[PDB]
Image (tube, rainbow, N blue to C red; front, side):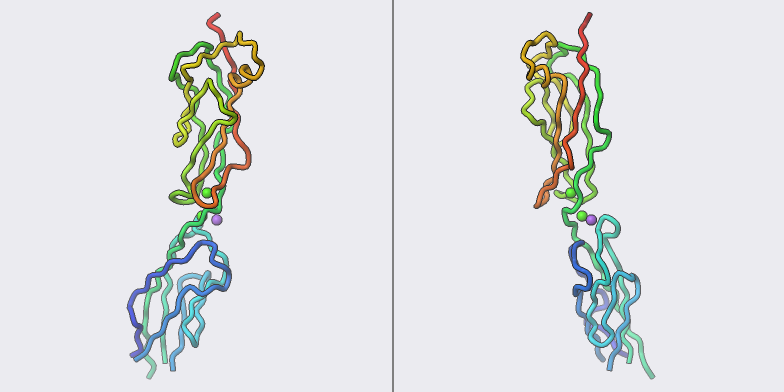
Length: 202
Ligand SMILES: [Ca+2]
Ligand SMILES: [Ca+2]
Ligand code: NA
């Protein structure tokens, strides 16, 4: 009544595993003909018990599969589950959420005043989905919490009556770029501008 080495099988592959690639090898005994049910993404070779992908997978669509595998020869069936888990691979860029950002700010607003919060999103997992945010070029007027996106003013004040054009530019435009922390790291297509409309206290 032909049965497998184990009743239940646990396997891990990577979301970029190729079309056709071997997932797992199964042998049952007490000849023997094998069949696999539970996703069309997977097929099992009927003589040899080799499970393979039929297609490309994607953990962001489906991270875990359960397949059911049957061995038959007065024939008798035997059943084992196979429990495929896809390991995340860093294959999505972050995407800016509500960019660009248009804001109105009172000049000489004091140290540590709220300005905005930039937000991006990454559908990958763990380090690959973790977002880190940076102001370029180095902006002396604004400080940004690299993990949370929140932007605040600095101990340097915002003075509209400042004659350096570049410092005025810095005051009135903030450019954030965002990465994620997998290897390779991936950045959002483009940076994201906060546009700042400076207002006196008339
Ligand atoms: Ca992924
Ligand atoms: Ca990513
Ligand atoms: Na993907």
